[PDB]
Image: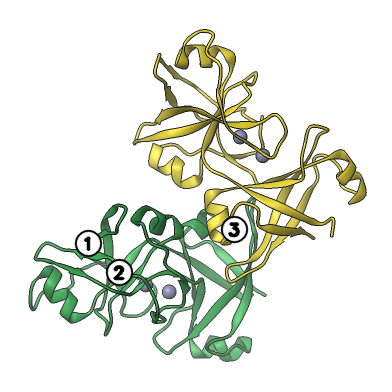
Chain colours: A yellow, B green
Amino acid sequence: DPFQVAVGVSNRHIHLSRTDMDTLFGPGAELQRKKAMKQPGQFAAEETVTLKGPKGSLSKVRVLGPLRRETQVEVSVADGFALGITPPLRQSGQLDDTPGLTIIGPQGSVTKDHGVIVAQRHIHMHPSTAAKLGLRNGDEVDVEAGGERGGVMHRVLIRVAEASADEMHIDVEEANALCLKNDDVVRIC
Amino acid sequence: DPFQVAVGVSNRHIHLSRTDMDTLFGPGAELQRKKAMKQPGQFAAEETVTLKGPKGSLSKVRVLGPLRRETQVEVSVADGFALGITPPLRQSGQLDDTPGLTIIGPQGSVTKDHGVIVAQRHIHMHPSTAAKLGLRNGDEVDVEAGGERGGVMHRVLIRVAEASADEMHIDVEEANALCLKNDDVVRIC
Ligand SMILES: [Zn+2]
Ligand SMILES: [Zn+2]
Ligand SMILES: [Zn+2]
Ligand SMILES: [Zn+2]
């Protein structure tokens, strides 16, 4: 069944620019791969940061490599409340009018004015697969999960790129709400 | 639309036996009302406890009144993970083969061998409403939630009792996963 995609539960994490990486970890510092992810080229790094908000802070927030053009922080709704901000629901890269935080690293700190979002659930899909299912990049779909806490998720963003592996990304709260874990199978409706 | 029902977002909390109330807060100690809930006679009390598990503790956990015949602890999956336990998904009062933890109050502590659960989402329903919708106690329904993070929750238990107001109860993670909040309106399918 080509409609079955595996689940990747995305914990809170951060993408860093080269400039911000230099500030937080020192000039010329390279991310060290800790664990390779399903999406090709992407990985969880050894490096982590502390996120400080007006209300509180979060420690050991994972940095995901590779480095990107713009810094982006992804936190759960609960994470936001603990920090003392209200990050809006957004797809990756949609950072206009988003709130900021203070990122703290070993070599320095940077207080961002934007880049913090709650991740909108989505499916990374190969263009081959997307072509089969008659799905276009930018589409939204329904996804069903089984089990004692199962249900159907609306507004699942379809993300098609050549450098993609078939996988669904949901944050920790979405996963727990449906009793989903890494490598669980869900179905596109 | 009579199939619509208001949402009550349920944060972690505890119900206490009289015996356990005596231990934690002193013999003869009465729960003090802070804020009444929508369910008749029930209320969030001024009293709070600390929950201690093998891995960590949670402070300021709300006690809900009135007292009951058996102590019951409701926590989210995330809460359980932080405590160092794995509570199963259960309906209220369904406490067979459940993990325990240590409850700490001002006057003493008690270590329970059972009674910790992750709450199964449910709808409290007055018999008149139940008769009008064609629902019975113990039935399970689907509930649709709208909005950017909307979707359809499966396996929603119907709890029919005279001392009930029409209201759906979901925990913090289920609420955040769907961007629901208190007094939001969802619809029974
Ligand atoms: Zn990300
Ligand atoms: Zn993703
Ligand atoms: Zn309860
Ligand atoms: Zn309830």
Q: Nearer the viewer, mark 3 or mark 2?
A: 3
Q: Please give the chain letter of the residue carrying mark 1.
A: B
Q: Which residue is mark 2?
A: B14
Q: Please give the chain letter of the residue carrying mark 3.
A: A
Residue B28's spot in the image, x, y percent? Answer: 8, 78
| Type of the residue with mark 1 | Val
Q: As drawn, is B24 to the left or to the right of A183?
A: left
* Cα distance between the residues tagged 3 and 2: 26 Å
Q: Which residue is mark 3?
A: A180
State ligand 2's quadrant: top right
Q: Which residue is mark 1?
A: B49
Residue B7's spot in the image, x, y percent? Answer: 50, 66
Mark 2 touches mark 1? (CB < 8 Å): yes
Q: Nearer the viewer, mark 3 or mark 1?
A: 3
Decide: few, some or many residues near mark 3? Use Cα within 10 Å; few <14, some 14-19, many ≥20. Answer: many
**What's the residue at 12%, 76% (across, down)?**
B22
**Beta carbon at label 2 within 8 Å of ligand 3:** yes
Decide: few, some or many residues near mark 1? Use Cα within 10 Å; few <14, some 14-19, many ≥20. Answer: many
**What's the residue at 44%, 36% (across, down)?**
A85
